[PDB]
Image (cartoon, rainbow over all chains, first blue to last red; front, side, top):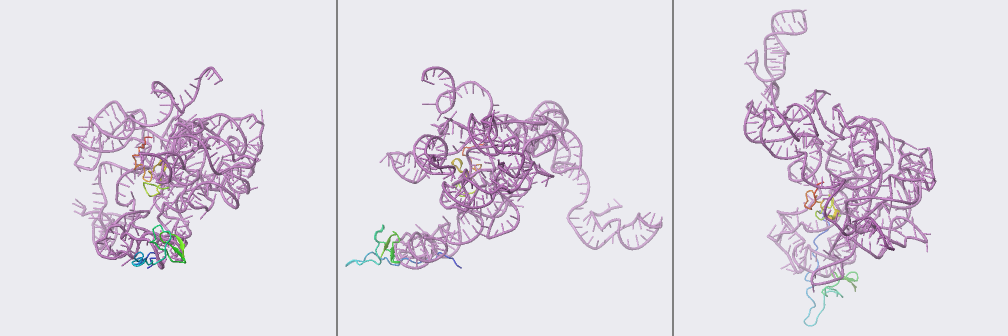
Length: 64
Length: 38
RNA sequence: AGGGGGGAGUACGUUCGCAAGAGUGAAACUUAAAGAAAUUGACGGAAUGGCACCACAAGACGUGGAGCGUGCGGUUUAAUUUGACUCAACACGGGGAACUUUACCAGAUCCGGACAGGGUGAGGAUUGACAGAUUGAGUGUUCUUUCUCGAUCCCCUGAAUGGUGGUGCAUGGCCGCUUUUGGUCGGUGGAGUGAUUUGUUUGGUUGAUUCCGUCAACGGACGAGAUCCAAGCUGCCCAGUAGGAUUCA
RNA sequence: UGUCAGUGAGAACAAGAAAAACGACUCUUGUCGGACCUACUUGAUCAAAAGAGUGGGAAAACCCCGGAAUCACGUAGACCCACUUGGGACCGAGUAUUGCAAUUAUUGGUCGCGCAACGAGGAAUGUCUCGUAGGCGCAGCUCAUCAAACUGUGCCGAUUACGUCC
């Protein structure tokens, strides 16, 4: 009774990436780590995996 | 090769003088102006 | 003398006969036809008249047993996909196929399952995704990570479409062959109860139901012939990519 | 094998038919050349296979639009009645070419093996009477690439019969 590959994933976000930078006294800063030089603006953020970071959409090599 | 008036690619493709009419046989599919008299 | 066909001229009895046999003569059981005549087809080691180097004569060239290519059969194998088998199978399926083509085999994938009518919008079963893993496939299918998200993709039914799957004995179209010969059919009239026949017939001629003649047939329609395509000779057209003639050189 | 006859050379001489165009670049007020062939020259101060540049064509233009096989040849060529110097099929090594991918795919190539078969081949059986049979070559076809196949054109070109129905 094995279907092998393909299943439901249920993943990605919840209410996470809720808003931009919170404000109304001073700006406090994002959940994650920055993306230098995206082409879709800085609303994209980079992975934490193996001390490397990677942009899942603009596909850059940048590390921490 | 491959054919453009079928997608079969088998039952033989004519590419002589830049035409295909042998994946739909020309006896059935005439009015190309050809005739037999001899 | 006979009362469907077999059983049977058998059985039993009885009379005749030297014997072989003769006369008389059932039943049990079984079967749905047996039989008569004529007609139209097919076949004949039947007859007659004709026609074909797919028939033969005379005789030129091969195949048939070698070494090769190709197809088929057999066996084999994971699969050795399959149609076709005297001729109208077998260098055939315009089929000289290696991955593609591909039926078939070894594995993975897609939605094409569209169509939401019964459900999940945001954050979904999702679209796209580096690394890690998955696995032949760092492939992003998948699973983890994290990112990119239209809400179409996704959930359940019904519905669906796609197919080189079978059936050519469901079928259309097309092709092969019967048949490369001269054959085919109706109206009106004649004959027969009818099925049928005459027309389409003795003779000669021709590849020819091609002709002339004749006749219970008369007048017709197709195939044949002819019209077409190509070749050989030629007129007219006729010249700058067609090619020669004379002189100058 | 002696009626191309087997290895060498030179001469004269053939006909249909195939081909081209990518939304790919560049070009403008609405757009041109590259996937076809063949020519010519380097490819020999040193092979073949094979590299590249220039040049023309949509074909009666493509260089003479058309050529080398059958054939001719005594140039006083070589072989010479042998399974060979007649034939190839197996087999190993090398290299270049084609392609999305080659696993002899490549194959027009080198050079081994040939002294591996086979000597016109039992019975049986095929099809043609004239420019035909037979012999020979070329192109088209299929298409990453290969034709002992198929289709078409041309060349050399007879013997017998022109009767019968067995």
